[PDB]
Length: 19
Length: 74
Length: 57
Length: 74
Image 1: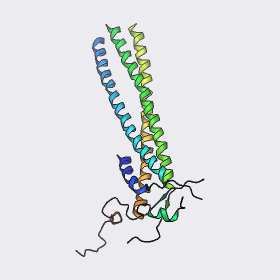
Image 2 (image 1 turned 180 degrees about the vertical axis):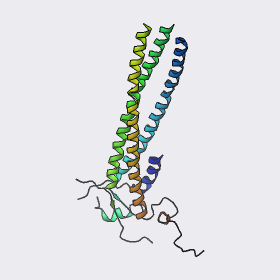
Image 3 (image 1 turned 45 degrees about the horizontal axis):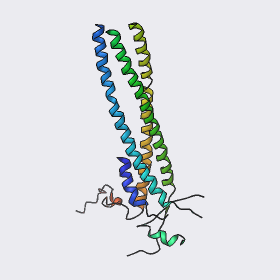
Image 4 (image 1 turned 120 degrees about the vertical axis):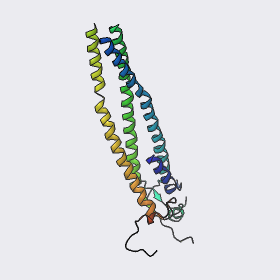
């Protein structure tokens, strides 16, 4: 559960797909 | 008396064989964790870029708006 | 009858001996995911923050 | 034959009693896992609050402070 909530935060925060 | 003790042993052994569904339930939990980690590694792999060797990822302020100004145009 | 009951006990002991390899496979899978969490912690520790040129509004 | 059967049962039971130290090893790996998860939570907490707009609606993440510095205007 802790990783799943950590995944939900890290999705919108980190990705901008630069490549 | 020995037969009574043997039936008691078999009775406790059936309880110890009940743990197989519990171990498979653990295996599904680690499998769910493995999917969550793999999505995280997929997300961190996209933001990683080279720095003018080191491969340091860069985060932006709002939606990667600063990433267009700083980085070299390809 | 007693000897037949003990052969049933050993058969259930053999099934529990099969359960040990499944437990050890769980331990190896916990170890592999723990190495994965360590290296993503490494990639999060090395990260750059970018600040834009103009405030949008 | 029954006594020889009991020695086989005891010997296989001792092979099953070797597994308790392995379960204790599962406990140490799970403890080391949640320290690593806590470090990941600590890193993402510092990033999302230093960088604006990345709260994901927690109702102003910089405003998580307790409010009683003898203020009471209300």
